[PDB]
Amino acid sequence: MTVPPLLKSCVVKLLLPAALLAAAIIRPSFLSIGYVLLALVSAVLPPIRKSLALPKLVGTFVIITFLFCLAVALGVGSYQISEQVVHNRSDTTLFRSIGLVRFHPTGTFESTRAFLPEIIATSAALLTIIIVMFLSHSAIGNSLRRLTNFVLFLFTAYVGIVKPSLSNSIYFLAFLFISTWWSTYTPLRHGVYNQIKKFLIFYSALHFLVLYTYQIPIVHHSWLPTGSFLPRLFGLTVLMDSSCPEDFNDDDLIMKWPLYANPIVVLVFFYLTVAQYKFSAASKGMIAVMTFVIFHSYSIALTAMMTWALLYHSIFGLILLILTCILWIFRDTRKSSFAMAPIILMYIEFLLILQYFLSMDIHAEIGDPAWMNFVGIEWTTLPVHAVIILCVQTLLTLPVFLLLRLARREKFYE
Amino acid sequence: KRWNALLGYTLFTITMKVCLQIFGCVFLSWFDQSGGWGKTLCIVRQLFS
Amino acid sequence: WLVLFALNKRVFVRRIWVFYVIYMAILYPLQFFSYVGLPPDSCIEYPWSYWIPSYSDDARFNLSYLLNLSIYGVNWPSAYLIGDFFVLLLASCQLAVFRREGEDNDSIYNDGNFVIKPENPQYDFIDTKKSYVDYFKSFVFHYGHWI
Image (tube, each protein chain N blue to C red):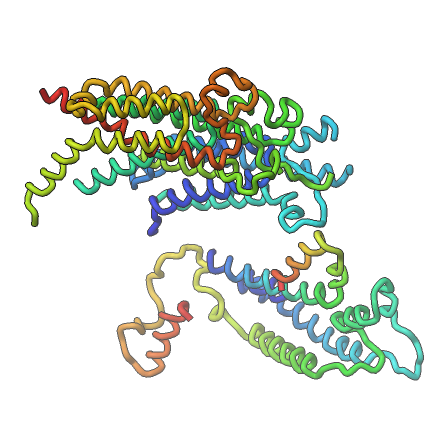
């Protein structure tokens, strides 16, 4: 009788997608579409909080999972049996695309792989049967919530950094838009925040769909080759290409951390976003501390701006240093920042988007125009260095971005 | 009915063990296969004792 | 035989116990004859020496042993005979009990309803403390399912 609704609901909503994604990354097929869709429909489902038993919509989604998983498992089993009884062509293309794979007796993770995905699907189906038949019976908190919103903001930045391309270009655009809205210190409505979250979740689901369904061997073999114009532009990388007896790009750099980390990083990003959607010295001491902070915020941001000029080389960087010395040469340093904060923000954001364009997954598509030989910022051919340098760039541009926040706040105080 | 079901299940497994005695003493030679299929049936021999 | 015995009510067992005891009392001499087998002086082979020629001699010997078919010069264990004899003893004595019997042994639920019966011949042993036999009765009819 002591049926834990929350515990078993969390077990479902977390582990069954987990083993689901494991059996998926094992082998890609139409099982990708169906099975990843079964995972992603749940998203942030209405919790079973001891009310109205299992939700009607949740129950409908779960019974759809029953039907689809049972049909897929039975079909794969029947097709494998038929192949065994009977036995690179179009029939073989459909053979890979459906979910079947050739059986060979020489694999620890390969001979089992011939039937493991359907075994895992049947096990998940049985667990769902058991669970559905069994379930039918703040100040520090607010500070931590804002801190986790900030680290989700940083995670949006990081997942934009890991694959600079049109797959994450919209991520970076949403990042900059919400950052500028939050910088004006105008309280952004919870409706707009919910709309931004919904757009992020929808485009993330589309991103999973395209990245994985493109990871199917047939798609990259037939429709368009791996690392072609669209993969170089939008961003499409195939991770696993090893198959049964009839693996990405090249291994000149052994690490290749961003390329291998893209799936798991974006997956944990999805999980964090859906979870967030569901979720003495007296006053004189820190008042003087905050007074010093507001009197030296432009100074510290400008020193970080120099640090950017040290790390990165450009005639733009020359413009950065000349604007730095202009701002730090006069008596009205605070007033100078107060007046030219929008201009420096526009310049730095343009520099961000320009180095992003220069760090796109595209290579040799634009060539080496006059803005390269004369100016000279690296193309970032290796992504391992690119991810680190652009993460340094954003963590450095954070305070020079906050200076406009403080300037606007002060500005509407008078 | 549940207790009689437990009775029937215990007698089911007693019959299965008695019938598997001969399956393991003279019918074990079907279990001397190669890897793969033989490996799987070797495991099921282990897990059916 | 055990499976057909257990999952059936006492009426069916009463009907088939004569058949079962006849079967056991026929098998026991048959089993002893099978253990004895043909004399080696006869020099006549057994049919089960060629039932499965595709296997080794050990497999054929074990197959004949589990079927309790005779093997030339094999030491049949006495435990088989002792166990079968004890089964025969119990079967014969239970047949004797079955012939001299009314309605005491079978279930009291033959009427059909499973609610508490109005009257029962024996007192409420749980509350009373007649003797140590009452203690044992309470222990085994109140916590026997635990065991």
